[PDB]
Image 1 (cartoon, rainbow, N blue to C red):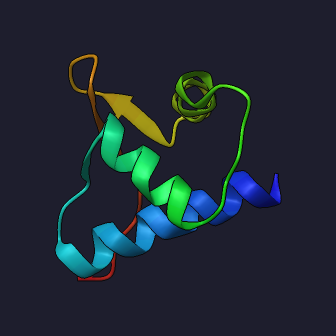
Image 2: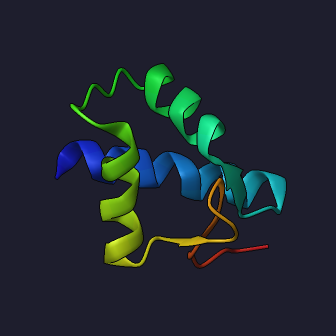
Length: 71
């Protein structure tokens, strides 16, 4: 769960700093690579985060992060 938490923390910070909660699938993958997250199946790792509520699909390739922000 530490890995998923670290990944969500990264998305939360990107969204806060950029005033933008939209991420394409491959952009999520690039962030995961930068954090050295290695999972068996990235698609269903993302799918699990969708199931948990962190990401909502906006079409099959794009996601909206569900987060509080400060700005």
